[PDB]
Every structure is written in C-alpha cells, then in structure tokens.
Amino acid sequence: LMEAQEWCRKYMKSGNVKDLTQAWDLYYHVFRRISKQLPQLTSLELQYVSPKLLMCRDLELAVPGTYDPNQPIIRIQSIAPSLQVITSKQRPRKL
Amino acid sequence: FYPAVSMVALMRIFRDQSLSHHHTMVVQAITFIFKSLGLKCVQFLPQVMPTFLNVIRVCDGAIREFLFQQLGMLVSFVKSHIRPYMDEIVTLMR
Amino acid sequence: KSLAQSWRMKDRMKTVSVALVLCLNVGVDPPDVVKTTPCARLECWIDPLS
C-alpha cells in the first residue's frame, strides 16, 4: 500500500498511466487477498481488535439504551470477550 | 420427541408434594430412559440433575439409600459429562 | 589385548521427509465421541472453532 501510494504520487508530478498500472497491480493484489480473508472473519476476539474494552470492568457509564430516570442504573459490568459477526453487505457485529 | 415428553412429565412430579409417595417410581423411569438412549441421554442432564441432587438433601432416609443407587446408575450411563455437577454430588456423599 | 570396541554408530540414519496427514474436519464431530460443552478444543495451540 505504501508502494502503490508512491506510484499514484509519482502520477501527480509526471502524469503517465505507466505509473498507475504498477499501483493498480498491488491494489488489486491486496484487494483479492483481503476479499479472500473477509469471508472467514466470522468472530472477532476482542483482545486483537480493541484491548481497552477487554480491560474494561465496572464502568459507572450505563448500558447503552437502558437509562431510565425512574429505574436504578443497569451499568456496564463488563464487555463480552469475543464478538459474533453477522454476514451481510455491511457485516454487523453481535456485541 | 418421546423421551423429551416423558422427562418433562416426570420432572413435573419430581418437586416435593406428589413425590411424598412417588419418588421411587419417577427415578426408576429416568434410569431406564438413560439406559435406553445411549449417550444421547446427555441432552437431558441439566434438566434432571439440579432437581435430583436437591431431592436427596430434602427427602427422608426411607428413600435415600435407593436414590444414591440410582444416582450411581445415572453417573454410569452419562460417564464424564457429569463433571459439572460433581461438587454437589461429593457434598451430598460427604 | 585391546577389546572389541563397539561404541560407533556406523548405522547413521537420517530422516529426510515428513507427511502430515491431518484428518480434522473442523466443526463436524464424528459420530463416535459425543464431546463435552467445555471440551478440549485446542489443536496445535489454536482454537479451530474461533
């Protein structure tokens, strides 16, 4: 990606398509690789993605869309250690 | 289907007041069910076992020597899958 | 009179190559062993199910 950025930036001083073909080589390269990765990212181990939330225990901050002025606060005791991922267009998490 | 229905009816009795007479009968059925199923019996464990162990502590000693005979029978069919409830069992034995 | 000194390993074998046949149809428990809920799911220091 650094190298494809270099070539697309060498376009902005020269303006040749011969720069751009070298960049789209590497771009399509990672595109195809990453396209072959995302189908199997079915669950996200929370340590790998966001350590602060794994570390998080017992926030005073309330569980989102629970707060009632007439109830006592049901507060975030702890976030779950791993996240199920729904497969759609937008790959939502089931946090 | 069939084992699941019977198990639910049996366990609906298996709660103090009706069992005053019909403990023994229920437990004889269960033990026969698990004996018959193989290892597919394992699915009913969390339904049966918590009530079962509480029955032993609650009931009279007239029955109690029998319940342990049948507990040991459940144990044998289930084998290693009983491990979650083992603390309670050992507490009961102790 | 020096002894029949048999300390050599003139039989110097060498392991050249390795097959890692590895039947491990992941997420498909074969009909023999019905596995536990918290079973041993590690497998060369990886949870395959994750």
Image: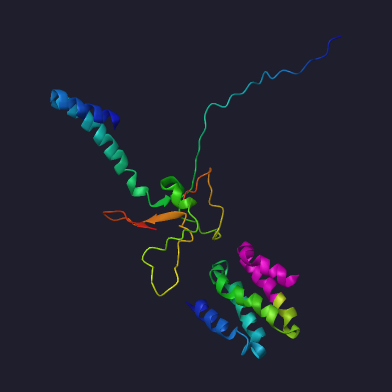
Q: Residue furthest front?
A: A69
Q: Quadrant of the C terminus of chain B?
A: bottom right
Residue B50, image x, y percentages = 61, 74
Residue toward you, A49 or B56: A49
Residue C23 vertical placement versus A85 (above, below): above
- Res C50 seen here: no
User: Which residue sits at x=76%, y=18%?
Assistant: C6
User: Residue at coordinates 59% horizontally, 73% vertically from top-left?
Assistant: B34
Residue A28, relative to residue A54: is it above or below? above
Q: Look at the image and say whether residue B46 sits in the magenta stretch.
A: no
Q: Is the magenta stretch mostly helix, strand or loop?
A: helix
Residue A89 placement: quadrant: bottom left
Where is residue A69 shown, x and y percent of the image? 38, 72
Q: Which of A47 and C33 is in front in this view?
A: A47
In the displayed structure image, the side of residue C48 where residue A65 appears, left or right = left
- Answer left or right for A73 relative to A18: right
User: What residue span does the magenta drawing correspond to?
Assistant: B69-94
Question: In which quarter of the view is residue C34 placed?
Answer: bottom right
Among all residues in the image, which is located at the extreme right? C1
**Res B3 visible:** yes
